Structure formats: structure tokens, C-alpha cells
Image (spheres, coloured by chain):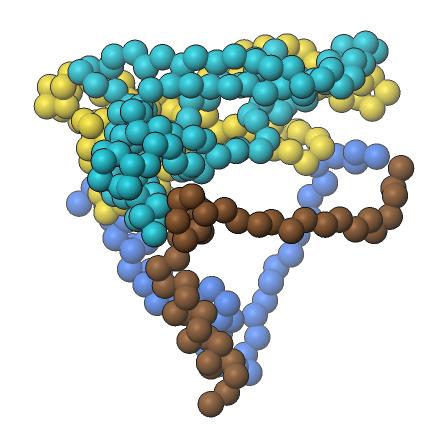
Chain colours: A yellow, B cyan, C brown, D blue
Amino acid sequence: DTEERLVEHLLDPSRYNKLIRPATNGSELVTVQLMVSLAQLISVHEREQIMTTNVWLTQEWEDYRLTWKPEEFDNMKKVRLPSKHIWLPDVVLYNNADGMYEVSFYSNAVVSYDG
Amino acid sequence: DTEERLVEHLLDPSRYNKLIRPATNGSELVTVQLMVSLAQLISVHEREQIMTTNVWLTQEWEDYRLTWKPEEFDNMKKVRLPSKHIWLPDVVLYNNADGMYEVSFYSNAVVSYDG
Amino acid sequence: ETRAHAEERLLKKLFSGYNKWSRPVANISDVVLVRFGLSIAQLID
Amino acid sequence: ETRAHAEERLLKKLFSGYNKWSRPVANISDVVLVRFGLSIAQLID
């Protein structure tokens, strides 16, 4: 019950906007910390020069307009949010072949009270 | 007639929210009983180390906000509902190759009045 | 007076309060009859 | 006052009366200039 009201409070279209990025203090840069972890190395087609891998890329970034008071919402530290709604920086293989560029599943994103 | 109004009462977007999982009294565990049934063993490609099989995985979980009074509506015991609308736990194979993770058909789900 | 204008009013009227996931039957005990048939365009392989 | 809020106000004002399919030109007789450019990432095969 409380999670529903909390998510409705955070993801209000009038209050939160998906298009513009968050920024403070005269266009300060928003740092994105990414690191890769490969689950299995599928194949290496040497004849076609193609390496097929299965990759999890974990991305961290700070965001200020998503902060909430944790004490009011029953002391919740973390909440799930759909990746399609909240803003996210696009990260894609720049030298990728075979057309496919972006990630597949668009998993849900964890959001802490700090932002 | 009563079936339509009952389904509309259950699946009201302003009343039921899919993005949040059910919980009572601060993150109590919701159990998920799943069991597998092997339809047939389709193929085994040992050259690429891939086993293609036909599987029916049955999932059962208790849910409380979908309950309804049976005495009010012509003593209806069970109702069918679409999968994409009601919440469903994500149970996909990890060691799965070929990228494909989630199930294909997204069949209807039976719901009893108990929950 | 045109045919399209009348069909538009019909389509607006019947889809006004119609549901998709409700199994359309008069009573709970009554059944439906799904006449089923096949045709083969070609036998690929 | 903050920059993000100003950009939000701009984006809200801008898309109020903008239609996608309409070809944006001052007059019908006037033309547009589409500067076009290519770049080769790689030659796959």
C-alpha cells in the first residue's frame, strides 16, 4: 500500500520529467560510473571476426529530484523503479557490429533514499 | 454480465498497480511454489552444446489485493485474467543461451476468491 | 445518410462498454461453440 | 530558477502547438535545405 503511494509520489509526470537530465549549480557534470561483468563467453567466430559475449553492465549515477524523506514512508531505504520511466544515460558499444546496439531486457532499477 | 463488471472491478488501474509487488506489514515474504513438467525433449546439439526442450512451469503464489467476496457475485469461485496486467514474478533461466529468457505465450491465469 | 457515417455510429455504440477479457456467455452454466477448421497453403518442408 | 526547471519550461512551451506531419516552412513556395553527410563505421562484409 505504501509502496504504491510512494511510487506515485516520485514518478508524477508534472513533477518529474523524463526528457531533460538532472543538473545543479550551473550545468555541473553528472558523473556516470559504469563497470562490466561478463557471465559467459559464448563464442569467438574467428572466420567472421566476431566475439559473442553475455554481459552485465552496472551503472551508478547521482540524481537529486528523486530524493524523499525516508522517515515519513515507513523507513524505506530502497525502491524498485521501471527503467523505461526514469531518466537514464544511453551506453552502447560504439564499434558494435550486427546492428544490435542497446541492452535487451531493460531490467528494473534500484533507487535509494539518497538519490 | 456480472463477470464483466467483476473483472473491471479487479483490474482497475487506479486501484490495482502492477509495478509494485504485494506485501503486508513491512516486507513479509510472499512464497512462490514452482514445479516443472517436461513435455518432450526436442533436440540436443552437442556440437554447440545446446539442449532444446519443451517445458511447462507451473507457478502458484498467494495475493491479497485481488480477493473478492464470492457471496456478492453469483457465487463465482474462479476467474480467468490476462497475464500482462496482473503482477507476475520474473522466473527466467540463468544459464540460458541464445539470449531468450522470458516465456513465450503469456497465457491466462486462474484466480480463486481466496487469493 | 451515407453508409460510412452509419457504420461509424454503430461501431461507436457497440464498443462503448464492451470488455475483452470477459468470456461472453449469457449465464455461467451456458457454453460456447467454436467451429474449427484448417486449410494448407503449402507444405514447406 | 534552476537550469533544469528553465529547460522544462522551454520544452513545455515549445511542443504546445507543434504538429509532426506538417512541413515547417514560412511559405509554401519556399524550400528547405537538408545538409547530408555520411560516415563509415566499418565494412562488415
Q: Is residue B112 visible?
A: yes
Q: In front here: B28 or D40?
A: B28
| Side (left or right) of C41 relative to A8 | right
Can you say whether A72 is above or below B79 in the image? above
Can you say whether B99 is above or below A100 in the image? above
Identify the residue at image location x=57%, y=27%: B103
Can you say whether C14 is above or below B74 in the image? below
Q: Quadrant of the N terminus of chain A?
A: top left
Task: State which quadrant residue B29 falls in.
Answer: top left
Can you say whether D36 is above or below A102 in the image? below
Q: In front here: C23 or A18?
A: C23
Residue positioned most to the left: A72
Task: State which quadrant residue D5 falls in.
Answer: top left
Identify the residue at image location x=23%, y=26%: A3
Identify the residue at image location x=52%, y=83%: C3
Image location of residue B78, percent across then percent down: 37, 32
Residue positioned most to the bottom: C1
Q: Quadrant of the C terminus of chain A?
A: top left
Q: In front here: B21 or D11?
A: B21
Image location of residue B35, percent across then percent down: 52, 12
How many numbered badges does the structure rendering display?
A: 0
Identify the residue at image location x=65%, y=15%: B38
Image location of residue A84, percent across then percent down: 42, 36
| Side (left or right) of C4 relative to A59 | right
Q: Is residue A21 visible?
A: no
Image location of residue B72, percent across then percent down: 22, 39
| Side (left or right) of B59 relative to A42 | left
